[PDB]
Amino acid sequence: EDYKIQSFDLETQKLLKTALKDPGSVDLEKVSSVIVDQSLKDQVFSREAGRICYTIVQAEAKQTNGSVFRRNLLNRLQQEFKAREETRKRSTQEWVCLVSFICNIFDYLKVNNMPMVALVHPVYDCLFRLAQSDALKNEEEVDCLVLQLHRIGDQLEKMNVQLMDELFNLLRDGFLLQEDLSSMGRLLLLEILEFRAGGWKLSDTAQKYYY
Amino acid sequence: DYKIQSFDLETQKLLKTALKDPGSVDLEKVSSVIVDQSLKDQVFSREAGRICYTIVQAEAKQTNGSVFRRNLLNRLQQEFKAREETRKRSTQEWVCLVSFICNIFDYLKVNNMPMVALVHPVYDCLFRLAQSDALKNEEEVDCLVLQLHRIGDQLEKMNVQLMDELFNLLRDGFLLQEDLSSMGRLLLLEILEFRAGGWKLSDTAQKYYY
Ligand code: NI
Ligand code: NI
Image (cartoon, rainbow over all chains, first blue to last red; front, side, top):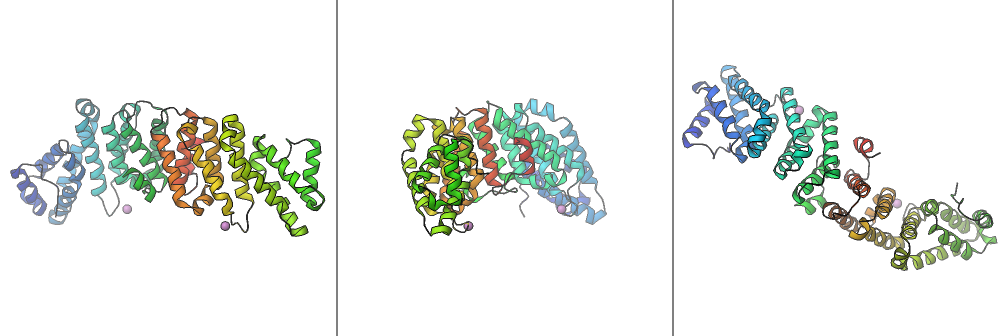
């Protein structure tokens, strides 16, 4: 149904819709390229691109037994991931979009509900970046971080619990020690600390307190 | 081990007699010496429930009486009612009083049925410790989290809405009140995680905090 592609050109939406049903009829390298381009420019699409990406990947595998789209999508994703520090320096918004996109691809591009190990290190590297002092000092980055933890924290922890323990240690540190967090940042961090402590869920009383 | 090292030699003897033979002592006096000393000694304020329980049971068995229990709880009430003036007089005496009340709650049971008469005295003390001005005092925060580690799960079952309200104050003090010390902030975060984990300390949190 809803692939959340409202932010694109009418013409580009037409291309994406065509890719969905008949990937053999489109240039899948180009399709991957327009998807990753827009994922950096639109908050909603950065958080929802996985829906259309999974559907094209499945369609291509069923049609031609091919993974041209996936390979091109993940190559481009790796290119953007590698340039994440310069992207963060250029634009906090493009950087938080990139993180949401990588994490959304992790969640949707599955073999069963087996995630792709190739995405584990990209996801963790981004979350660890967000958990540094000089990122927690930015409320936009904290919002991004906790969105990913709500979305895929439980799955990620399974993929590597020690990394998750180390990540949450940074979160306690930032929460405990670092003075220059906004009220909204401090609140987001406390909620996610309670969220993991409760087994990646929101108790009724915490729901009422925060929301 | 009844943790009575802080008493005089003569009072230690009275207490050891009372445990074995409550019928041969002035039980009103025994309760009096116990509450007096619970305000004065940290270790005794946290452990007096042990000896209190034992005398209560010794007396119920020996004479079917509750002179000790009634006199102990009467005196506890008198101290509880005087809590504001006690806190203003001595922060140390006040946290000893909180430890003592919560220790009596934990030990003076029927089944493991706590006494409802102790529920509001316990909660009132914890709510006082959770106020902005008390959170600003590291000694009061240490007292608060000790009680919550000891009897929080038990208390919550008595009245969950009060526990929910108490933890709302803890989040508030955590989030908003600037004048907490690094130790106070550490203790509060641990108790928040502790309750959220079902009154349990995760392995990773054990390592982080202890
Ligand atoms: Ni799975
Ligand atoms: Ni019980």
